[PDB]
Structures are given as C-alpha cells and as structure tokens.
Image (tube, rainbow, N blue to C red; front, top):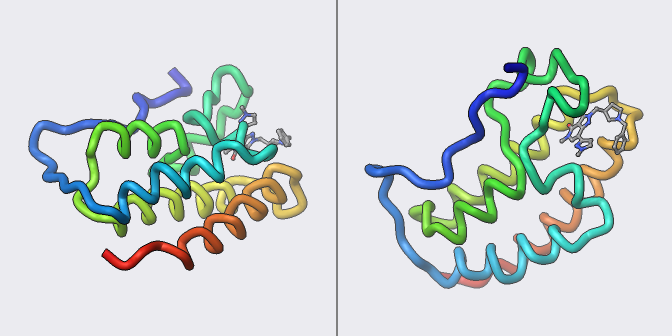
Amino acid sequence: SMNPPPPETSNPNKPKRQTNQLQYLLRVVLKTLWKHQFAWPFQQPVDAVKLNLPDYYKIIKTPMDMGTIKKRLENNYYWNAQECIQDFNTMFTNCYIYNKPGDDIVLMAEALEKLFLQKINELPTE
Ligand SMILES: Cn1ccc(-c2cn(C)c(=O)c3cn(C[C@H]4CCN(Cc5ccccc5)C4)nc23)n1
C-alpha cells in the first residue's frame, strides 16, 4: 500500500505504569492540543493514499500522530511520561522533516508545538 501498518497502541511485552504525569498528559496535554483548531491534520496517521503523498513514507520512517498517542495513553501503553513526550516530539519533527518550510501545515505544527511546550512546562512533579 502507500500506507504502512499504523504504529502499535498495545504490546504483549512492553511494560507499563500509571502515574499522575501520564494522567495529566491524557487529561490536560492531549486534550488541550486535540481541541485546537489546528489539531485535525495530527489526529490520525498520515493517509498517504487519501492525501496523494507517495513520498511521505519514503521519508518518514517513524510516523506518529495524536490519535496513536491518545490510544497509547487510554491503553496504559507507557512506562513513564518521557516515553509519551517522545511520541509528541517525533510527531512535530516528522512534520518539519517532510514539509516545505513555508507550508501552512508547518505553521499548524508550530502552533501546536508552542502550546505543547507550555503544557509540558506545567507537568506536575511525580
Ligand atoms: C488529514 N490531513 C490533511 C493534511 C494532512 C497532513 C498531515 N501531516 C502531519 C503532514 O505532515 C502533512 C503533509 N501534507 C502535505 C502538505 C502539502 C500541502 N499542504 C496543504 C495543507 C495545508 C494545511 C492543512 C492541510 C493541507 C499539506 N499533508 C499533511 N493530514
């Protein structure tokens, strides 16, 4: 297909924990970004077939998106907050790798990244 299988949202072996920080990442951080007017291109895996982007998965080998992150949080997939933060960060840098710098999709990502940094600056102490 052009589309790879989507990133997993569960795993038989990967260990997990629940923490107040992971709860905050779902209830506050993911929620705040998800409701933003510019969230919609980031709420699901890039569908290269639908969007006609034959080069996307030639370039992006570690895809990530907030739909996957939301499911990972809901499924208790993460061991700690750092693992979840890493997924957000991958989502943003993938956008900057793939896209032309002046593209509106990059402007959208940048607005969401600025909000994300504000929210992570208030990550509660564990
Ligand atoms: C559902 N959906 C629509 C677009 C995407 C999308 C998501 N991600 C993460 C991306 O990194 C995308 C890259 N594209 C192609 C750009 C070329 C012209 N731009 C034009 C453009 C600008 C602003 C918004 C949409 C399209 C879009 N499209 C995407 N997902």
